[PDB]
Image (cartoon, rainbow, N blue to C red; front, side, top):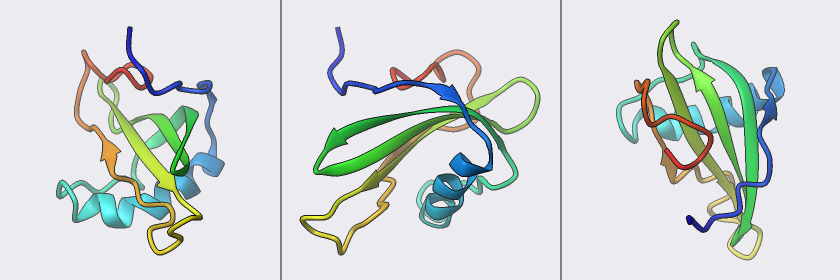
Length: 98
């Protein structure tokens, strides 16, 4: 069993692309990623020190990347601080258990 509480995981459109465009800046220079050129097909969400969003987005035609966009409130300073994510995978990029 794994904690977290991934809320859901429905289809994703450019609305997840914003959550994706909001973290791809930090995600770009975090793991030298890039995002933005990927299509988010679905997403989920969790509740912790604020609110995060997990996304099942792909970056080609045989690979997926799960990002972890996180928003706070009690320490706004962070706000949409995607501190978790994964890219270039085709075996452990399922939902959030990636």
